[PDB]
Image (cartoon, coloured by chain):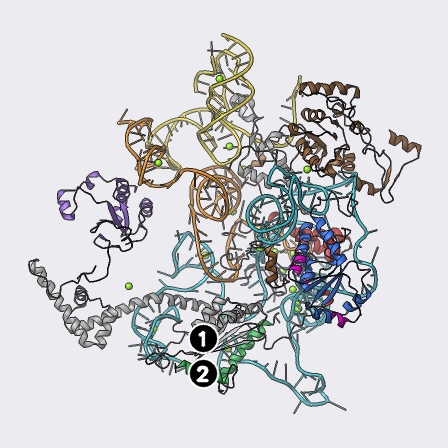
Chain colours: B blue, C red, E green, F brown, G purple, I yellow, J orange, K cyan
Amino acid sequence: LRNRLTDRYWRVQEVLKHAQHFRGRKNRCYRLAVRAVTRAFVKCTKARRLKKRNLRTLWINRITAASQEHGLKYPAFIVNLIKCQVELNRKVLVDLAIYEPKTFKSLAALAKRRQQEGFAAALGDGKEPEGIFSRVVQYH
Amino acid sequence: VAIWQRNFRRISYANTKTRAEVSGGGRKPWQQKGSGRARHGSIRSPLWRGGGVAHGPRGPTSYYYMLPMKVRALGLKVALTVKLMQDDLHIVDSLELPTADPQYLTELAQYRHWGSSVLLVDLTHEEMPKNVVAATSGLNSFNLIPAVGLNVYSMLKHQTLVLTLPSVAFLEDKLLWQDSRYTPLYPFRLPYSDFP
Amino acid sequence: AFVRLTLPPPKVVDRWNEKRALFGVYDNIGILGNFEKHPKELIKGPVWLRGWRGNELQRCVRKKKFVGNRMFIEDLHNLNKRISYLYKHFNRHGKYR
Amino acid sequence: TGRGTSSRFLTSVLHNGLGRYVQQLQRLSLSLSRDAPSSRGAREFVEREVTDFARRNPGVVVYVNPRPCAMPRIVAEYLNGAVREENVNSKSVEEIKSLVQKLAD
Amino acid sequence: VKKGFRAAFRFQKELERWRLLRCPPPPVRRSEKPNWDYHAEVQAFGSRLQE
Amino acid sequence: GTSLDLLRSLPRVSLANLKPSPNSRKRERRPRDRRRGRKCGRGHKGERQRGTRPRLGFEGGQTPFYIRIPKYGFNEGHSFRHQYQPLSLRRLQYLIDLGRVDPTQPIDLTQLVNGRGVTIQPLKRDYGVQLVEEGADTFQAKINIEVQLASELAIAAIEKNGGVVTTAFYDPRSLEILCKPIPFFLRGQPIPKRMLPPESLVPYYTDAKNRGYLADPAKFPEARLELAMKFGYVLPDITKDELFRMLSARKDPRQIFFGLAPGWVVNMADKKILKPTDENLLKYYSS
Amino acid sequence: KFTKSRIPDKVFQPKPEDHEKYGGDPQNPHKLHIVTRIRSTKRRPYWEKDTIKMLGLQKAHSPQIHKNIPSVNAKLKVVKHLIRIQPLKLPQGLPTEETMSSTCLKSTGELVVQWHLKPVE
Amino acid sequence: LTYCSTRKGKRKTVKSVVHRFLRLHSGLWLRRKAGYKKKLWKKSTARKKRLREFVFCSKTQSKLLDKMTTSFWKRRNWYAGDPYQMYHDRTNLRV
RNA sequence: UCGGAGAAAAUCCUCCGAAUGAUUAUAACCUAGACUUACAAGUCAAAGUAAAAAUAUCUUUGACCCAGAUA
RNA sequence: AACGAGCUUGGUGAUAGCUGGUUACCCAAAAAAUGAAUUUAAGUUCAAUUUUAAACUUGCUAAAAAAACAAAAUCAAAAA
RNA sequence: AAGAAAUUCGUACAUCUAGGAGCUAUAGAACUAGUACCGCAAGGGAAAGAUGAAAGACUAAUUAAAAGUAAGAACAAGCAAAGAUUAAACCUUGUACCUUUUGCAUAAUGAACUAACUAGAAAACUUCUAACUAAAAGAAUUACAGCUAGAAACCCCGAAACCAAAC
Ligand SMILES: [Mg+2]
Ligand SMILES: [Mg+2]
Ligand SMILES: [Mg+2]
Ligand SMILES: [Mg+2]
Ligand SMILES: [Mg+2]
Ligand SMILES: [Mg+2]
Ligand SMILES: [Mg+2]
Ligand SMILES: [Mg+2]
Ligand SMILES: [Mg+2]
Ligand SMILES: [Mg+2]
Ligand SMILES: [Mg+2]
Ligand SMILES: [Mg+2]
Ligand SMILES: [Mg+2]
Ligand SMILES: [Mg+2]
Ligand SMILES: [Mg+2]
Ligand SMILES: [Mg+2]
Ligand SMILES: [Mg+2]
Ligand SMILES: [Mg+2]
Ligand SMILES: [Mg+2]
């Protein structure tokens, strides 16, 4: 045996250190531990993408709850705020709903205000002048 | 050159027995079928404890090869230049010394800012002075060789080179002969018109 | 895996022993000595591979050619079998035809 | 590895920037070998860059210890009590300078 | 017995880590530990706070 | 040389600072990692993957290409054909100009070999050197040269400048001694006789037009003049030439060296030549 | 057999109502095309794959400027279904060396030569 | 073939190649046409002429014949009066 | 095994033949460029030269080795 | 103590176009399973593909008329 | 597939008993032993040991350290984890590995687990790096820019059988 590997202790500990919080022989038996660690790492990597999407779903639910309190559906709240040139994102809208209820009510009133102008505008046929809150600030 | 000097002498005596050379192993251990075991034909196969080695060292092995004669001569010229340009070469008229005490030689090396190890070259082994022979005999890092013994590897191992004036002429003659020479019609040990 | 629980004794190497200090001397015996001797003549080793190199089949055949007539019966039988195995490997087996 | 590891919340040591900003790195130690190939880049760092780093950061105490050494090592200590150690073995001058700045920040 | 001094040396460091966990050392003031100069540290204290 | 000045600045060269020339070493790949491990480059399991594919030239069972072609005597008798190293007049002039061949003395295969102008391999069926016409236009040397074969144009160039060319036959044993005389001398044998040409080559070396060494001298003047008229030059009377004695020198058909008779022993060590006195031996060598 | 298709010429002969709908004059035709890839060439025949790379439309929703000349149009007709063709419009004229660095292509198809990022005022 | 021979440890020539093909030094190989001596009474005159010719070998065939012969057969031979003297070299070959 | 024909470039798809003879104005040698083709084998051919004073006309197959027959 | 032919050793590392296996990381490219011959169809050799390096110049898409066919591919001027 | 000879070369380290980019208890001899044990016989054929200067100092210590257990059974829900979370489990996401099968796994093989051992090897041509260059090579070889040297390569286990001599 001229040349025998002498570092196998540390190569084994590379895998087992990640497996110590498993249950069963997965947490201490290298042949089983290595297979489990590889699935845990694959799950972690794919969960990084999924985490962003799940957070957005949480925000939309929380925004729907907040807007429904004032009588507005989620699509009405979002689109009409956009039509007012307000670019607050869904993550920030949740922070305002939970921690700034008075400000969020103003946004609901603004969104409903713009929504009503749109209803009148469509029936207006274009002869009627544009709504006060329906004006767009141009940029160049 | 230095790698040639190290690797052309090398013979490794590492060996292992193949499955054919380990004691026993002739009979088939158990039948192919109706055993529930892995199939085997000998208890000395590489998979077994005590079996033969599949690809191990085989017998005495040699690493012999030869660098071209011009290449090996060119290496010595490069090594001599390196010692001179790096202020590690010291030309001396003769190796005569006042005393035979090895301490004197070591002290002189310190005084002149020579290295921890010194290589001393003399023209021929037979005529080398008695005083230097005694001094170098007991010194590990001061080594005395004749001119025919000069080589690249020893020059690298020793920090400073000491050449006598006659040795320098000897060295120039042999090395410069290598360029401006013909290829050999037959080995140079045989008589030639103008070669000693 | 299990590891030593103690440090092994330190290895002490004398780099200036006579063998290490004088390694390489007379490797230029030919060019610096008028070519009376070739440097290979300074190689110490088995009679059949002094100043020679080859693959294992060549080495086995060379040993038999040199000292085959002075070999023990066990050794010579093993050497001859090694030749036939290597002969079949090099001349019939491999990726490249 | 998230569930196999610890986590914490975003924080500062002592409300670091509310009133005035204080540099958390307070001590750097550099161990060198005078004559060793692996410590060459660290030796060049001391010759050229260590003095400038010390002047730029007057609140960090820098200790340079040339001594017989197999691997050069940088030890960084912070005000909160954390200690970080870095192997500098055979790194170029730029890498060591780049790493040293990261410890300060 | 596998060849090598290095693996033995590595595992010694692992042993030290385990020993510390089981029987943690009694805390010692930084003045006792190496790489300490009182005069320089005092000046750095002032410079740190911009005072 | 500024490069040597760079060495002055740098640290000492030693066994710890050595490096091979860049790109002088490729990497050896072992089948251990996933890239080159696994199937290890042998492909899927089969005859080739197990290492037992048929021999080179086997085409899967159909009659192979190298066997379906008829046998024909391209190389019949190849090892028994005589080969002549070609020496051109261009190369001969180059050697004379650089001093590697001495035009003052007669030129034989030994002189050409000594000056490295030609490389002879007797073991590889060389029977000597043939003069080759190439370079004839620019050849301007007066030379006495002995070759095994010669061409009409090559002979014309030699004679026009005032030199002499003869074609002589050396047997395989004689050729080796002529090419490398000194190794022969160290053996300690007496100089052997030179065998006459095989019956096939007798007509060639007994013909004046080829300047054969066994040809009739009386027929040389006619042959020499004929080339002069054919190739438009005036034949030079070489007897008047001061170096006529050297130019006229020719070896005896049974002599290998100019001044050494068959049967002598060359004692190089003591700088002596030993000659036999036994009558029967002298008859053998004189023959 | 799925094969390359030759469209009848009548498809590309417009009607008077078409000019009113899209607001393009049959005279003074526009010079440069704005073309964007809005579909994938996966699951499409290789000839459609080839032209998309020739036209530079490898990335989707990134506009490419092309010449409104018959040879280019022939290639565009091959991949007409995978792209959106919009006429390049120059309200303020061609960009000059001074304004070459201040341009911006609007979603309307207009290449403005002055881009300020300020309220119109 | 034999890559490492028992006695000398060398490659061995396939003599059936040496008995059928001629190697020109440039790297080309010559051969005869199969059947050029067979059943000539039923072959057309043009067919017989095609059979009589010496023909070159392809790159793969040349590569195979190179593997099946040793270096001795690839050397320069200076035969007096060689009839292939001119065909051992390539002229005006740009490629 | 190969050739002819339909489907029409698939088929265990459907047919006819060939391992030919007849016919003779006897049908050379040499040589550009091409076809066909895994390889092997198989096709067409200007120019030049030579016999004569229009080609052969109907319309296919077996390699290497090895044995024969001769001048 | 499993005889269509005992057992042991040796030849022997028998041979196996068959089953199984063939141990670090990173980067890049990638066929196709088509045609031909083979006691050949569980294999092999050649073509074809693919690939690395090098040389120097046109390639890919398209492609009018116009022929060849019968009354969407082959060919590929100019251009783009 | 096999394969000469003629003919050239070679005084081999010489001196005295030396040497290792050989193994270190599954290695290196099968070996602590041809023993124990197995077979009527020929024959086959193992395993293992570890204190200190002193045991005429009571036999040493050293190590979160393998699997396995114990200390400490479990608590709706699910390839056993991942995202997370104030929170271990609850909520959400998620059809074990290898090998093959057509690129397909709810297929079919193989794996109770731990430790150690356990499988790519050669230089004809080609490429890269250098020496010298119409010549290169330390004799025999190649050469119409070559020649010389270096570096770069082609696995493991497994039959039924066949033959010789013993029992
Ligand atoms: Mg999403
Ligand atoms: Mg055996
Ligand atoms: Mg047996
Ligand atoms: Mg077996
Ligand atoms: Mg063993
Ligand atoms: Mg030659
Ligand atoms: Mg062909
Ligand atoms: Mg004609
Ligand atoms: Mg029985
Ligand atoms: Mg086998
Ligand atoms: Mg098969
Ligand atoms: Mg058959
Ligand atoms: Mg074109
Ligand atoms: Mg043992
Ligand atoms: Mg044992
Ligand atoms: Mg445990
Ligand atoms: Mg659950
Ligand atoms: Mg089954
Ligand atoms: Mg390898």
The verdict on a common chain for dots 2 and 1 is no
Q: Nearer the viewer, residue A4 or C42?
A: C42
Amino acid identity at mark 1: Arg
Is residue D39 found inside the magenta-colored segment of the image?
Answer: no
Answer with the quarter of the image where residue H82 lies: top right
Measured in 3D between alpha carbons, the distance from the residue under mark 2 to the one under mark 1, in whole angstroms, is 13 Å
**Residue G103: quarter of image:** bottom left
Query: In the image, which disc is placed on residue E43?
Result: 2
Q: Residue furthest right?
A: F278
What x and y, as percent, mark residue E37?
Answer: 50, 83
Q: Secondary structure at mark 2?
A: helix
Dot 2 beta carbon under 8 Å from ligand 16:
no
Q: Which mark is residue D55?
A: 1
Q: Is label 1 within 8 A of ligand 1 (CB to nearest ligand atom)? A: no
Residue B147 placement, left or right of G20 = right
The residue at 76%/67% (across/down) is B136
Q: Give the amino acid at mark 2.
A: Gln
Residue D93, compared with residue E17, is above or below; it is above
Chain letter for mark 2, please.
E
Q: Position of residue B50 (x, y in %)?
A: 63, 65
Left or right: D72, with F109 as reference point: left
Question: Can residue B65 be seen in the rendering of this structure?
Answer: no
Count of marks, rendered view: 2
Residue A128 image offset from top left, x and y in percent: 6, 60
The chain letter for the residue carrying disc 1 is D
- Position of residue I59 relative to residue G14, above or below, is above
- Part of the protein shown in magenta: B78-106
**Residue D69 x %, y %:** 57, 74
Q: Is residue G105 shown above or below F190? A: below
Above or below for K82 versus I21: below
Quadrant location of the N terminus of chain H? Answer: top right
Instruction: Quadrant for residue K53, please give it.
Output: bottom right
